[PDB]
Every structure is written in structure tokens, then in C-alpha cells.
Length: 124
Length: 105
Length: 258
Image (spheres, rainbow over the protein chains, first blue to last red):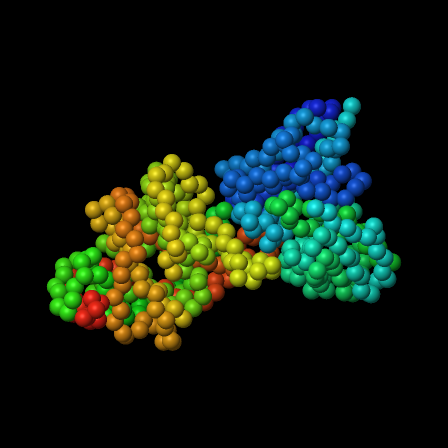
């Protein structure tokens, strides 16, 4: 599969964005989807994760309660709502397949397929 | 949960590099490793502490034991100059290492 | 979930011979030494039962004509369950029997079964007897009624008889050790009931669920390294026949004729 990100753009703090990651093939239904962000000059950092069927959703502590993830296998797409953005959330947001269909299996694979991330700048 | 990596490592081309990843009893977990060329998407090079994805050269060898999981590059060459991120899943929330740049002289 | 594996493998079917097998107790009344004649759905003696192999991933949607006899050699626990249903899709209520490691879960839902349903199995390094199972059976499971959980149903030959009569789904089993190289044993053994589920659905087709290991990982395939252990399962069909069923002094069925 191949992933293409979209929806990342300039926004003032407190705004809202809806990131979209439309997969190349329909085998996207079999990958737990992961959102991982790379700060502009810092290391790689996990953000959110969703099970293959969307029934297991986990967030990092730094975004819990503000982001909500979803996926639509019918449109072979992944979504991330950014509610109440802050400045320290500026990054480039990758969508990465995991391979395991449930949270009990996420550790047995790796984020093998990575879409070319889309930059999110949260500033004035 | 936190993972520690050295800020950078440097080896001569053709030698053996070693990027380390120390964590709180990490050896009981599966530590996957990623490679990120400057300004490009990360590429999974080792997963399950020993297994490589298809297409990753066999010179990419890693291991996990105790508190520390290490990645060793045999025959380090010019295309291996990139950032390497240890990764583990704790309480269904993944954690990424600091990222140790590797410089190939 | 819903990863599909079987691209093109289309090797023609192979049939073994269920010598004298799939004979159950068609009653819950204890009988002493007496030759009893029963007329129920039995697997005919010396009938050609198909010989499926797990290593070709062999998850074909098979007809559930009147009741099936399912037997699997299965030196390691890879045959995990079944997906009995009429359409194996939405808009049609379907049944799912699977057992993880220590319990069997039976559910009758409006399942949206995958094209190649199975289970991924992994052994975590903290305890190499964990066998963490991931469900690649259905994509959606909603709007349903039944749910049953008990001890697991399951070279360790394991035989089953599923028949769906008058709203009850009846399951029989007899798990016995086997040393024979490839095919069914010749000795007689009588299956005895496991459960009697008040299901009340329409069943016309069924499909088995394998437990596949992910041996290797190409980056994007999802269908890369699903190796399938080594086992074989045997599907026969029940027909209405009249057996003369001999009971031991202890109440056990030691022999029968067709």
C-alpha cells in the first residue's frame, strides 16, 4: 500500500484541523493505523493509534482529550481531528500502517509503511 | 515510559556501527527500529528485536536483552547516514527513542 | 482486519476414507449392554471425506448440506473454529465458534466475514506459551443476540459433528491421540455431545478458521508471510441413515453397523 497525507496547513493556536491519509489500495482495512509526528527540529514522536476495525483507540498523554482519531475503510482513509491546538503541537504528521489488527498485536509488528508526512504549523 | 539513546554515533565507512537503546526493563518488550534519511519518511529496518522487513539488507542486525536493545550496522556505508529510532509499546502506547544520528565518514 | 491470502492456488481436491467414524450418541439416556437401532443423521461408513491441508491455507466456503463431520489431525492447535452461516455476510445472521487458549466463544451475529477468515498467532517473548491470537475473521459484528463462553472445545486427532435441527445447533466431539501417519484411524470411537445451543438460524455453508503465523513482513503487502503450521482437516457430510448401535456394559458405544 501507499499512503498520502492531506489536510495539514497553517493555523493559529486553538484552531482545528482534520488530517486525512488516503491509502493507495483497499488492503488498508487490514492495518492498524498510527499517527506519528516529527517536530521540526526534534526527534520522532508517537501521537495516536487506532485498531484495524477502529474499535481500539489509544492516544499519547500529550494529546489525550484534544485529538480524536477515526478511520473509514470504505473510503480507505484515516482521519485525525485536532481540537484545541497548542503551539507545541507543530510538527509533520505521518500516518503509518502497523500490520497487527488489534492493540494486543501492535507490539509484534512495526510501522512498516509510512505516508509522506504533511506539515502542521500552529502559530500566529 | 522513557527510552534513552546517545545523541549521535560516528563510524568510518565499512566498519561496524552500534546504536543503543536503554529502557526500563525493555528486554521484556519488542523493540522495533526505524531509519529516517534527512527529510524523508522513516523506514522500518528491524522489528521484534531481530527480524528485518523484506528489502532491508542482512547487514542490519539488532538484539534486545535486559534493559538495553542495540542495533548494529555491519559494513556501514554511505547510504546508512540517517537517524535511527528505537521503539516499543508500553500499555498499548508506543514510545520512540531520542534518535541517534549516524555519520558515515 | 480482513486480509485475503489465497491468490491462485487451485490444486484439485483430494479425498480420504472415513473408515468407520463420526458416530455419536443420538440420545441422552444411558443404555446398558444392548444393540440399539437409531435413525438419525450419521456419516455413512467408508465414505469419501475431503482431505484439506492447512499449509495451502485451504479456507474454502463449504456446503453445510444436512450436518458435517469435521476431523483434524492437528499436531499443534491451528484449527481454531468455524463460521457457520447462510450467506456469511451482512443482512444474514451467522454463527461463529472459536476458542482462544483457555475458553471457546460462541456468537451468533450479523457478521461481515472476511473473504479469507483466520487468526494470527504470536508468542510473546515474555512467556513463550502465551499464544496471543488476533482476529482476522470479520470486519463488523453488530446487531445480535447470542453469546456463549465455556472451556475450549479442543498428533491429537479431534473429531466434531455439527448438525442444525429444529432450531438447536448440536456439537459432538472426541479428542483422541493419533500416531497414524496421514489419514483417519480405523478404530471405532463414539463422539459425545459438547453443547446444545438454542441458535435457531439458517445454516447452508460453513468455513473453517486457521491459526497462521506471520513469518516475515514485507512493508506493504499484508499477505506476505502467513505460514500455516502443518495440519489437515477432514470434512464429511451427514446423511439420514439407520445404524444398529451397540452399547458396552458401561454404556459406551463400542461398535456399530450401517
